[PDB]
Structures are given as structure tokens and as C-alpha cells.
Image (cartoon, helix red, strand yellow):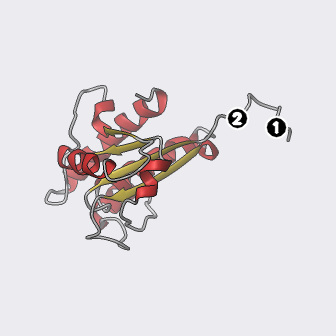
């Protein structure tokens, strides 16, 4: 219908979720955030993605263990692992990472580019329960993936509502 039917559209917001590999934590946060925005009729106002600080996993689907967790929670992930680019720093409002090694790495990168538009933060800096670090489940088990998933639901929810 009309462009004046509802309140006037917001400029698109963008968020990129990042870990070292882009197979475990970051695709899970991406698919969690994408569900939220899709369920709330606002996916057309978001550019949502995920990427890796390194090229070790380029082209690979998500970790099968994380995929099984997400499938339990009804959010199957459809993602091809990719490495962060220079353009990403210029194009995203937010780059949200999982841990401290991630943040040091991205901070190194941010200083090699001409325009860094993005606010670079830890995702868990949004957790109302104050669990700052979202711990790597790569060497863990099914309850470690569940933990990450639950942290991602709390943090993506608070981020959506109220960005830093």
C-alpha cells in the first residue's frame, strides 16, 4: 500500500557479528538476531551478517553441533563462512564480537582502514546478566553451545531494544 500508511521508515541499520572462524558463535548470533527482526516485521530495516577475523574456515557451513542446537530451537542456520573485509568497517553501524582476543584483533584491523564507521564492541557488553565474554564452544559439548545460544538471545534482544 502507501508509503504513508504506517510511520515513515527508518534508515536501514546494520550489524555484523564476528568471531575468529565464523562457524560457531558468530553465525548463531546472526541467525538469532535475524529471527528477532523477521518476527517483529522489521527485517527490511536491517542488514544482518557474520564474518571471521581469519580465513581458516572460508566457505564452510556452520559447525554441525551448533546447527543441531539451533535446529532444536527452531532456527536453522544458512551461512557460508567468510572473512571480514575493509569495506565491512566502513559499512556496518555495529561490529559485535564474542571475546577479548576478537576485540584486540578487530581493533588492530580498524586501524589499517581509511573509514571505520562501525562501533566495535563485545556482544556480551549488552547482557543484562553481565556475562561479558561469550566463551568459545569449539572444544566444548552440547551444553556449551546451549549456553552460547541463550547468551545470544539475551544480548541480541537488549541490543535490538537499545544500542550503545
Mark 2 lies on a secondary structure that is: loop
Question: Which residue shows up at 27% across the image and 48% down it?
Answer: 146
When the figure is inspected, residue 125 is found, relative to residue 39, above or below; the finding is above
The disc label shown at residue 96, or none: none
**Can residue 79 be seen at all in this image of the molecule?**
yes
The tag earlier along the polypeptide, 2 or 1, is: 1
Mark 1 crowdedness (10 Å alpha carbons): few <14, some 14-19, many ≥20: few
Q: Secondary structure at mark 1?
A: loop
Q: Find disc 2 in the rendering and name its residue.
A: 9
Residue 38 visible in the snapshot: no
56 or 140, which is in the foreground?
56
Query: Of all residues shown, which one is farthest toward the left?
Result: 139
Residue 71 lies in what quarter of the image? bottom left
* Residue drawn where x is 86% and y is 38% of the image: 2
Task: State which quadrant residue 132 falls in.
Answer: top left
Residue farthest toward the right in the current orientation of the protein: 2
Q: Cβ–Cβ below 8 Å for labels 2 and 1?
A: yes
Left or right: 152 with respect to 30?
left
Considering depth in this image, is 57 or 85 the residue closer to the camera? 85
Quarter the C terminus occupies:
top left
The residue closer to the viewer here, 31 or 147, is 31
So how many labels did they put on this image? 2
Mark 1 — residue? 3
Query: In which image quadrant can residue 72 be found?
Result: bottom left
| Residue 97 image point, x, y percent | 30, 46
Q: CA distance from mark 2 to mark 1?
A: 8 Å
Q: Residue 22's spot in the image, x, y percent?
A: 32, 60
Q: Residues within 10 Å of mark 2 (few under 14, many from 20)?
A: few
In the picture provided, is 21 more to the left or to the right than 28? Answer: left
* Position in image of residue 160 (x %, y %): 47, 33
x and y percentages locating residue 118 in the rendered image: 42, 42
Q: Residue at x 38, y 66 (%)?
A: 82
Amino acid at each position: 500500500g502507501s508509503h504513508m500508511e504506517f510511520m515513515a521508515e527508518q534508515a536501514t541499520k546494520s550489524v555484523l557479528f564476528v568471531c575468529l572462524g565464523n562457524i560457531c558463535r558468530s553465525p548463531i548470533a546472526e541467525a538469532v538476531f535475524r529471527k528477532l527482526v523477521t518476527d517483529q516485521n522489521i527485517s527490511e530495516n536491517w542488514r544482518v551478517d557474520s564474518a571471521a577475523t581469519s580465513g581458516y574456515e572460508i566457505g564452510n557451513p556452520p559447525d554441525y553441533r551448533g546447527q543441531s542446537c539451533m535446529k532444536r530451537h527452531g532456527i536453522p542456520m544458512s551461512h557460508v563462512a567468510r572473512q571480514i573485509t575493509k569495506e565491512d568497517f566502513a559499512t556496518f553501524d555495529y561490529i559485535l564480537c564474542m571475546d577479548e582476543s576478537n576485540l584486540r584483533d578487530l581493533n588492530r584491523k580498524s586501524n589499517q582502514v581509511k573509514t571505520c564507521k562501525a562501533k566495535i564492541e563485545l556482544l556480551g557488553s549488552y547482557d543484562p546478566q553481565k556475562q561479558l565474554i561469550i566463551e568459545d564452544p569449539y572444544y566444548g559439548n552440547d551444553s556449551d553451545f546451549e549456553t552460547v545460544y541463550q547468551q545470544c538471545v539475551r544480548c541480541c534482544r537488549a541490543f535490538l531494544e537499545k544500542a550503545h
